[PDB]
């Protein structure tokens, strides 16, 4: 049991004896690594304790595969779970530091981007907190996706620096390498089996990132792969001949696999890279898993037993190749018969779909996949025939016209001849999501509504063939990180008023506050914790944005990907209006009409999404004009927080008042940010889509600002536009002409306002009904104004947001996955 | 004071808590790193203890700059010096290992190639053993020079793998980075000073390799530089556009600097790289040094004081740019006046020449150096004018014809106009060695004879201008590594018969054996230690060469660079003859005539040295034919040890009988291998050149086989050849026709034997007098045969080799440098 003094010794020890700096003084950078490595000593004891048990017991284990994990800062949560936040903060005071300044140093480990990541991350938290044997597998990205710079011109992008000095967490296993292969050819041995040789050979090496659980010893892995070449593959002959580039070809191709997340794929090159990324993650991971099986088996190796021991969850369509791969392994190497193998595959692999719209499901070039994975392309032609012959066995061929509709929808091979058929240059493609349904024993959406959309729209024919497959597992975000750690003054309120700490685990007890939401003592405590959390943000803002804001205003946050469809353009238009009105006022009138506000925008645009970037540009120009208008004072501020990520969120969220999720209704599959915002008492404003539904519900209709069109209407409202039947509001045109006046800088936004106007055109005619939803929105904002003025009401609305969250704990979501897909029971670690 | 038990704890601790492997079992690879890091804990305590004192005292410090250090295996010597060889070997037994199998793992750290390196290495040993404040500065080579593979075809080359897993010794200082610059332009500020901007900017980062001293706490650094780029220099825009190569340009150029040692320089590219390598080492090192000065100074910074605190020794012509650089710094940044600066430069910088033949001294392209270092090229034109105007002040211009001879020899700028002159397309070059004499306060050769060659041939005119400069510092090799550690059964004999251990330090006591060389007890002990050491080699050989040899034969070693001029061709010809004669014999006769022998060859050829490679090829073919001739048995074996290096040597040397150094007399500047061989009782056979002289002398004429022409004769003997006045021996033609018969494989060596024949031609007519020296050599080998048959004699000859070595301790060589060039006194570390 470590004490503050023992820890101080550990920090010192590392600071000197395993250093990455000069030995002079104890500056922050050094202080972090020393502190971090001190933690990691503990993390390892448990990682080993855990490894041993999982190994000796030989029970089932789950393997969560994801192209992205968005782990963020590991430090505070690592020490939190260990229950040492106090010994560490005292030992750091002894060494002339404070914990928050030490945590400041750590970069966000950039191995992911979006919810897809953050989910996968949250999940690992749970999986370990609850003692469930499961690892995460991912790529180890050098340069993340990118870092965002907000400048006079808008967004600029620069490669991430997180591994500049290296990561103090990761533990490199050099005896864990697996061979990967691309290109080359296949041929049949005189034993029978097929043999895939030639092309390129590279290596994949394991780096384990420990994950510890809250109040438990259970410590699992996020094993990230790193691609490279053996040194011998350096061409000396050429390097010395002068051709330096030519000599590095080998390792440069082999390494670029792990450079950036989601590489540009416009060119053939980008595509091949993407594909490599995928196949690597798959083959590497599976290989490692199989090896662990074999090892744990000993003499009694029963391939029968595989799916009873292992479960592989493809987080979206990326890890798809797990299927043709696991088959290839079990056929060409393990030497089992096609069926036996296919059985084991189906019974191990599971799909988790994330997309709403058939077209967001990934489709590959045949000739490409052919040329890169030519053994896999054969296994995929065999799984397409197994399907074509079971669609012939069901339904039959009385209809012919319906057997052709069934085959067209469900066949994995697009634009092909059928095998043996009856009926008396479009480019060949491979549908991945199709292959995912066919191979896996389970398919799951991520929200009630979505999981139904998959059954009754996305995968209909499939649903009817195997309805037993389809499931739902509504998203959740971990409360450790998103409450207990990121928001301590709330966490104290919560512990006091529920009477124990146990709520960090037993998150249901969140609801026990329902009965106090009226209380004036809890109200004051609540409003005090929320200021407290905002005070920290005023500083961060000053710093990163260059703007001073008051803490006595509403914090109005829209942090999520900058896309037309998320409709930041809407939020800002909402601001632009509230401003314009302010200007046509008096001082007396202004204070009366509007409440003091700080409208926080955040998130990353594409690179070549001309418009997305023109928006961030707009937002900044708006803010500029406003924040430095002398008449506005502190009644309104508009900033744009640069380089939004886990940490940024860990600071904005605990200090939000209102959080927008105003995406064109029905397009959003779930959402995670809200689930957080909710937990921290933030009041949400949104259209009725994704989670917005399930949150609104769980928290109460009178605790969530709704507005705009709904799912059903959209087809019709787009028809109205399409026929020249839309009449805009006159306040919308008021904003539009105001921008064309030049009231926000000399930057011309005529091409921005262009995409809003017309009836037709790929980038015209306001496809996302910003014009349509505008009135209902700005009206809804008046209602927020109204609501905030009643502070007693507002505070209650907040308290209830928190009380109604407890079902969005990832703990729940996982329990569901663990019990209803993977079939894994807990493992106690004594 | 660590005990075996404390060490075991340390090894365990690291094996688990700072690992580079999976946690399963304690296999050798893991066992090494754990053991090594355990050592490095100790190394650091001292490195810090030492750092503090050198820092607080602020005395003078020396800085040995070298393009190559050949450090070899650090482990055994590190523990040796610490006096823990025994605690470590016991703790490794506790963990189910033995020390020698643990040491087996460690790769030779490949940061160097030849003596030039090994010297620099030996020196650091001393410098620290004797408590002299001095560091080494070098480049940190990723792939060394190369690894040698000996195959059916001969030598192949593959990039070194030493950093494959990373080095457990090196300590990376991330807060130690200095900016380097190439290309770009210069311009004059309106303050006066010159400003060099533009081109390329890169970074150089310090990695400290500790060196501990024998029986002392004094632990200094071999600070190696690593070149790189800040992450921000990764082109996201391009990478995502598809152009992956284009995006990495920045770091690929910046990194390739530290890839391989001596890159091929035939092409313009190779040259620029070479130059970069140099300038980096220089600027980086100096910057670091200056910084340490400034820091140690505080308020009282006196630039006057610089040379009184600092000394920089350019190990050969490589680190030359230290001069124009230190000037540039002291002028453009420190802002001092030209003279004051030039004074400080001369008084700090010192040259150590290594070459005999004016043409082996490095000369650069002007337009190249111009375009790469254009600020330095100006400083070099100013130092050339300072010289031209002092050659005008001395001598005068009564002669004119002699002032032109003086200027032509001594001017740093080759092929230029003079400034202001009297006298009423050859490519512009920069002579580096010339610049080295001009800037430095000291110039030194490496042997008596050589140091005279520099005064009276190489640098004559210069000698007469400033004869006060010229020195000698004869080479030495450290006895810790090359006796006490690499040869323990001798080391026991030595400790016993001298009566204390103190000889490891006080190496003079080696001579105390002179009086026992007759003794029969010491003789037996000596012959027993030498077998013992050979037994180990029989095994290594079997292993790496694939040949089983007896231990009861003479071990005849020629290990050094494979060059025509080192004349391996001679040794082997010597074998070929002794063989041929064997064949024309009977069994009775053979045993009578020849002694049992194992002729060991080793070392690396160039890549594009067609002949050097054809030789290793020959040697292997010869060996093949012989070793598997049934008539020869164990009377003769010829092997070729692949990938000769420090470790190979640490094994061959303690077990040599005879060691050849048979290079065409007078061409060799010193030699270090012999100095070792000597120390270990090996009897040398050689021509009278370099060290051969000083060794022969110190050990006794009747203890060293001499042969062949001498220095003076060579011009005349080449004249005899040139005029068609050479008559070959008839045994030489006997060998030559025997090879043309095809007695050694089907491989045709007609082009090999070609280079021996004729009168003229760049690659013809036996320029290296192999034909001429052949008779005298093979005659000399009969004398070795004779000598070995008398075992009592032979053993005595051996004992005396050892007794007469003690002046070749690097301890001596350094003391000399320390006292007579650098002016540095000892620093005790309590």
Image: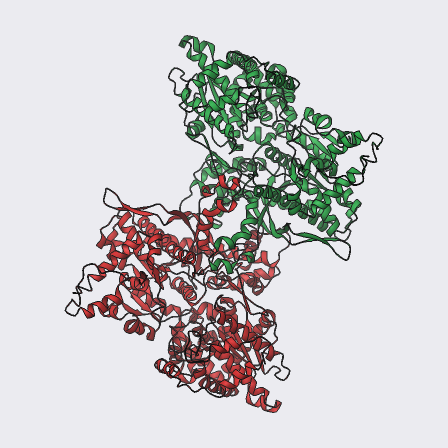
Chain colours: A red, B green
Residue A301 in view (yes/no): yes
Q: Is residue A253 above or below residue B444?
A: below
Q: Residue at x 37, y 72 (%)?
A: A669
In this rendering, would A273 be left or right of A17? Answer: left
Give x and y (percent) for residue B795: 55, 16
Give x and y (percent) for residue B686: 58, 19
For residue A469, which quarter of the picture? bottom left
Give x and y (percent) for residue B460: 74, 28
In this rendering, would A510 be left or right of A591? Answer: left
In this rendering, would B73 be left or right of B710? Answer: left
Residue B223 in view (yes/no): no
Work out whether residue A11 or residue B280 is closer to the camera in this orientation and state it.
B280
Give x and y (percent) for residue B723: 61, 16
Q: Residue at x 66, y 18 (%)?
A: B712
For residue B391, which quarter of the picture? top right
Work out whether residue B660 or residue B554 is closer to the camera in this orientation and state it.
B660
Q: Is residue B398 above or below residue B705?
A: below
Going by the picture, which residue comes out furthest to the left? A398
Q: Is residue A565 above or below residue A176?
A: below
Q: Quadrant of the N terminus of chain B?
A: top right
């Amino acid at each position: 049991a470590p004490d503050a003094a023992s820890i101080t010794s550990s920090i010192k020890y590392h600071a000197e004896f395993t250093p990455v700096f000069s030995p002079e003084r104890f500056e922050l950078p050094k202080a972090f690594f020393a502190t971090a490595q001190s933690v990691r000593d503990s993390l390892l004891i448990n990682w080993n304790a855990t490894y041993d048990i999982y190994e000796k017991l030989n029970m089932k284990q789950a393997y969560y595969l994801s192209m992205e994990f968005l782990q963020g800062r590991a430090l505070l949560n690592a020490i939190g779970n260990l229950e040492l936040t106090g010994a560490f903060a005292e030992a750091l005071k002894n060494l002339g530091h404070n914990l928050e300044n030490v945590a400041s140093q750590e970069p966000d480990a950039a191995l992911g981007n979006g919810g897809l990541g953050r989910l996968a991350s949250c999940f690992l938290d749970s999986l370990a907190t609850l003692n469930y044997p499961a690892w995460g597998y991912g790529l180890r990205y050098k340069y993340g996706l990118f870092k965002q710079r907000i400048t006079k011109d808008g967004q600029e992008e620069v490669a991430e620096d997180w591994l500049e000095i290296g990561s103090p967490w990761e533990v490199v296993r050099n005896d864990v390498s697996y061979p990967i292969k691309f290109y080359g050819k296949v041929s049949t041995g005189s034993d029978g089996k097929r043999y895939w040789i030639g092309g390129e050979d590279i290596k994949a090496v394991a780096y384990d990132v420990p994950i510890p659980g809250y109040k438990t010893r259970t410590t699992i892995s996020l094993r990230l792969w790193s691609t490279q070449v053996p040194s011998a593959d350096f061409d000396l002959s050429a390097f010395n001949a002068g051709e330096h580039t030519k000599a590095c070809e080998a390792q440069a191709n082999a390494e670029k696999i792990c450079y950036i997340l989601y590489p540009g794929d416009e060119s053939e090159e980008g595509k091949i890279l993407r594909l490599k990324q995928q196949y690597t993650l798959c083959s590497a991971s599976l290989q490692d898993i199989i090896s662990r099986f074999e090892r744990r088996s000993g003499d009694r190796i029963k391939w029968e037993e595989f799916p009873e021991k292992v479960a592989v969850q493809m987080n979206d369509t990326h890890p798809t190749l797990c299927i043709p791969e696991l088959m290839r392994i079990l056929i060409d190497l393990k030497g089992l018969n096609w069926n036996e193998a296919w059985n084991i595959t189906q019974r191990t692999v599971a799909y988790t779909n994330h997309t709403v719209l058939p077209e967001a499901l990934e489709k590959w070039s045949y000739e490409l996949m052919q040329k890169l994975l030519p053994r896999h392309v054969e296994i995929i032609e065999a799984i397409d025939e197994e399907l074509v012959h079971e669609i012939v066995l069901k339904y039959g061929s009385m209809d012919l016209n319906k057997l052709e509709e069934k085959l067209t929808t469900m066949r994995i091979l697009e634009n092909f001849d059928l095998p043996s058929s009856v009926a008396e240059i479009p480019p060949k493609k491979v549908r991945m999501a199709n292959l995912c349904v066919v191979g896996g024993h389970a398919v799951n959406g991520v929200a009630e509504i979505h999981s139904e959309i998959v059954k009754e729209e996305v995968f209909n024919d499939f649903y009817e063939l195997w309805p037993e497959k389809f499931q739902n597992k509504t998203n959740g975000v971990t409360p450790r990180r998103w409450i207990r750690f990121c928001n301590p003054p709330l966490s104290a309120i919560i512990t006091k008023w529920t009477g124990t700490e146990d709520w960090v685990l037993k998150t249901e007890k969140l609801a026990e506050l329902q009965k106090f939401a009226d209380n004036e003592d809890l109200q004051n405590e609540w409003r005090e914790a929320k200021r407290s959390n905002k005070i920290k943000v005023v500083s961060f803002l000053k710093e990163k944005t260059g703007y001073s804001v008051v803490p006595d205003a509403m914090f109005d946050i829209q942090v999520k990907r900058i896309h037309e469809y998320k409709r930041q353009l809407l939020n800002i238009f909402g601001i632009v209006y509230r401003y314009k009105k302010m200007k046509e006022m008096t001082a007396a009138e202004r204070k009366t009409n509007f409440v003091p506000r700080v409208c926080i925008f955040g998130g990353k645009a594409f690179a070549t999404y001309v418009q997305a970037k023109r928006i961030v540009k707009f937002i900044t120009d708006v803010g500029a004009t406003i924040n430095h208008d002398p008449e506005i004072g502190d009644l309104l501020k508009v900033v744009f927080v640069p380089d939004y990520n886990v940490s940024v969120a860990e600071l904005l969220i605990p200090a939000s008042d209102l959080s927008e999720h105003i995406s064109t209704a029905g397009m959003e599959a779930s959402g995670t940010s809200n689930m957080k915002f909710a937990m921290n008492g933030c009041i949400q404003i949104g259209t009725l889509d994704g989670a917005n539904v399930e949150i609104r519900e769980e928290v109460g209709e009178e605790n969530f600002f709704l507005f705009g069109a709904q799912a059903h209407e959209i087809a019709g409202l787009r028809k109205e536009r399409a026929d020249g039947k839309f009449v805009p509001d006159e306040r919308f045109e008021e904003v539009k002409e105001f921008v064309r006046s030049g009231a926000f800088g000399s930057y011309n936004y005529d091409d921005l306002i262009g995409s809003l106007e017309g009836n037709e055109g790929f980038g015209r005619a306001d496809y996302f009904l910003v014009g349509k939803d505008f009135p209902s929105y700005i009206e809804c904002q008046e209602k927020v104004d109204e609501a905030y003025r009643d502070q007693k009401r507002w505070t209650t609305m907040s308290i209830l947001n928190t009380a109604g969250s407890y079902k969005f704990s990832s703990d729940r979501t996982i329990h569901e996955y663990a019990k209803d897909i993977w079939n894994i029971e807990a493992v106690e670690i004594a």
